[PDB]
Length: 134
Length: 137
Image (cartoon, rainbow over all chains, first blue to last red):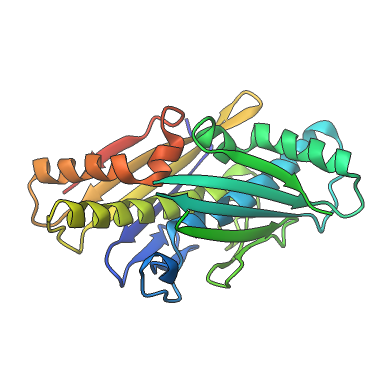
């Protein structure tokens, strides 16, 4: 059984949208210029994946923090870079943890990666590279 | 590599996730169902649902061009993404449901499989997530 279930519906075309069932997400879709699209103000699947993965890792840092009773600086960030290759996805996650050593930060990244469900979901199919930022 | 997206997420209740180009500028909230405050911000499962549904729509676009086929429009893809506890790990549960006004069931089912083959989210989650493909159409 699911502890929580989210739902979203997308339409097609150049006037496409993707929209959650609670309206928390209510977004337009545009194909990026770089891919031959109109490059409009709408988002796209890779950018949504990047925002979600970054968010998922932040969630996972909280889990790790509570389980191991370790303090994660409040201004820590995770940046996900997601490349589309011709189709497969490529991912780099880079965390910045103000005041921690490179060794502590790297331990946090590896621990988060074992918890985060996006990491579990994409295991062995997507090269996910973990980086720490000075 | 034909495109790269970037997003940065912060933590701590006032959490956000934001793309480098300002197209996404989202607040994050933990759902009441998992002990959060149920605020108006989105969450990772919801972002995955929105992205996977969008990816399937792009894949339908790819399939129609390559196969010289016509996908109605008013055609609709719904992703349902559930969070499951798996020991100390978590896992995603995913179903994708298409509706294609004016297509036969066999035609709609054809399209769902074709999209599933092409969609990079499907490639990414292959053999890890037991994806369910459905047609309401």
